[PDB]
Length: 107
Ligand SMILES: Cc1ccc(S(=O)(=O)N2CCSC[C@H]2C(=O)N[C@@H](CC(C)C)C(=O)O)cc1
Image (tube, rainbow, N blue to C red):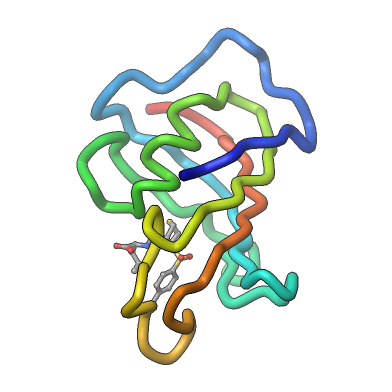
């Protein structure tokens, strides 16, 4: 599944509604802690509609629990990410992923 641990608390009241656009900055790391991709490296946040399956299950459930301004660590089992296949060229097969995600705004 996906486990969430807060790095910096959010407002504790503004949570995403289903289908709402979540604007985030994230850094994804493999289990050895090495970054494989980060929106911060592009200086542009990443956006997705909660529950529209634009992101892995780990994010769909992990970000659902977060509030605006919160920055948290999401640890995601492979089956909640890319499973046995992984994603060629960046994420190996059977990879547990750890993301540092900051929910910046809800539109
Ligand atoms: C090629 C690539 C680059 C970054 C990542 S990630 O940071 O893990 N990454 C993008 C940040 S959202 C969390 C996850 C994801 O859900 N990606 C989307 C679109 C991606 C694939 C464009 C998907 O799996 O459909 C996965 C795969």
